[PDB]
Length: 70
Length: 70
Image (cartoon, chains in turn blue, red):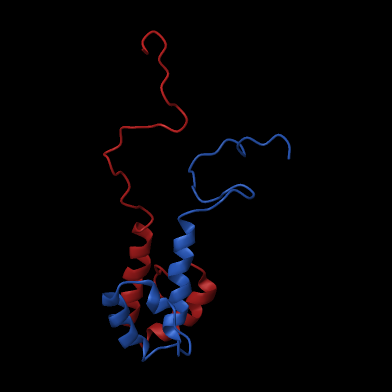
């Protein structure tokens, strides 16, 4: 359990952790940004309902969908 | 000198992309790896369900005959 700051590499096949661990050595700070990038899209796969989900754009419009009260 | 449109940088959180671009200059190949990583996890959203090819569906229904019993 003697590690400075590792965990992302322990969340995927050894084949990937090998090619990554070798390149990361050069950019231990760059891989940090991408680490959050891949996670961003990961959660995007599932989004609960809080206050109307926006994403699907439409060419023609008519109204603001069903909205009578709150 | 202002680039002609961009992908996977202008859409996503441009706030972070700002620091990524400067880093990408150093590791133009490394980013290529993380690019496939984020896309890989995306497809992972699915699983290898179905065991018996789907058919049975019982939860709280044990025998419901009447005419025949013996």
